[PDB]
Each structure stands twice: as structure tokens, then as C-alpha cells.
Image 1: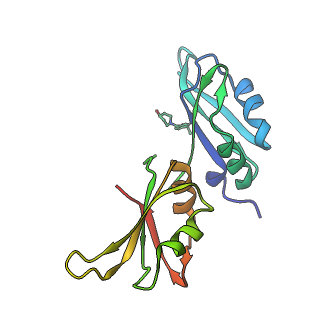
Image 2: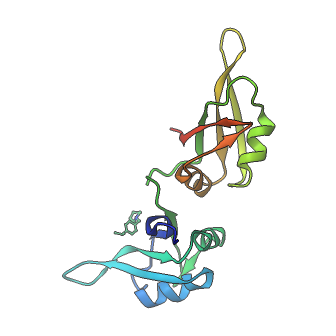
Length: 166
Ligand SMILES: CC(C)c1ccc(CN2CCC(O)CC2)cc1
């Protein structure tokens, strides 16, 4: 069974207006099989709108392409992003971690999604007791995008609610 097509797409902004279906494809085929590759254009002038998308055969290929950023395509650094259910943020809210979850639990789990810069385990302003949620800040938005499309996150035995923050 193939992963849903929506999860295999990269939406690419910042294209050179000279980039074509063919040159976008030749670039991004370096990181996987492309089942689709389109540059968006004006319907009357055919002038590029400056963005397009590609569709890989697997999610691992999307990962490979995203790990190969920055992408310079036809002389211009472009901006690829995956689809989320774009709100481009580097921080997540992690809820449901109760009082026994520590920083290393969150680090050990989330470090495989991306490079962590901040872990903030939330505590009560009056008592100092843990409140049962945390925020994790990464150095880049793709980590967050990968995280929030998962159906499940289990951290320290807890089923966690994870969403984009601010
Ligand atoms: C499916 C197709 C319509 C599509 C839509 C949107 C993008 C990316 N989007 C994000 C940044 C904006 O400034 C414009 C580009 C790429 C492709």
C-alpha cells in the first residue's frame, strides 16, 4: 500500500521564472522517483507564478529531498515544504506528559525529527509542580511538519497530543 499522495508532495516556492516542469524534475529526481512535477503558470501569459510542486513515490524520498536543502534550482535557492493538515513554525506544543516526564524523555524522542534548540517543560507559576505539557523548539520547520502529521506520539509511556505552537 502506497502512502497517501498528499504526504508525498513538496510544494516549492521561490522558483526562478525560467524553471520548467522538466528542469524542476531533473533537479528533484536526484532524491527519488517523481510521479508528478509541475510549475504553476498564468493561464493566459504562461509566465511562471514562481512556485510548483513535485510528488515523490514514497515519504522517505520526501525526507531525502528535505534533508538535501538548501536547494538551488536553476540558480535560485527555492523553498520546499511538505503538506500539513502552510503555517511555518519551528515550535510544538506537547501535551499529556503528566508529572513524570523529564527533559531527556522529550529530547531522546524528538531529536530524531530534527535538531532541538529549546525544551521547555511547563511548571506551575505558584508551586513549581509540573503541569503536564511542554514546548520543543527546533532549528527548522520540517521537523515540526513531520511531527504533526503523525497519528500518534508516545513519549515516556504517555499518548501525547502534539500541535504547532504560536
Ligand atoms: C499545488 C500548487 C497549487 C502549489 C500550491 C502552493 C505551493 C507553495 N506556496 C507556498 C509559498 C507561496 O508564496 C506560494 C507557493 C506550491 C504549489
